Image 1 (cartoon, rainbow, N blue to C red):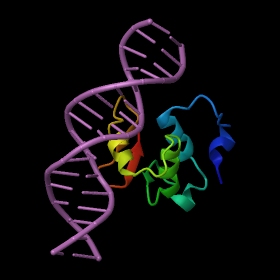
Image 2: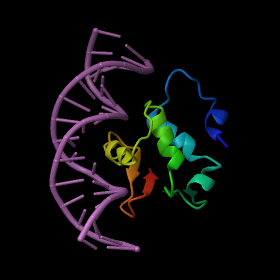
Image 3: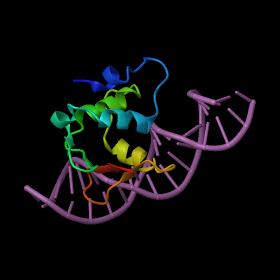
Length: 96
DNA sequence: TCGAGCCGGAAGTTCGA
DNA sequence: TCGAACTTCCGGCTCGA
């Protein structure tokens, strides 16, 4: 149920790239049971990132991390050209 | 009536080549 | 060693049941 370290064989040393990590988990088969991955073009909707958020804060060594941290940090992620936010709903995420 | 989610600017330490 | 990178910090706004 963890196509993460099972597919790319994640090493315990040398943290991967942030958007690469999300993108790596993005193509997760179980994401359907923990989130919504439509099988059409390329649209990703966050229904209940309960484990995704905890894991996001787990790498940061924190007990519980608020998802607002993603909106506050991820939004500021407009550094170059990678994950853009969709002006649809407040939970719609998309990549280009 | 009441609380929850949403995000602007700022600062500071550390990463890969 | 160089420049850049992501996180955490402070507090204000508005809608739905």
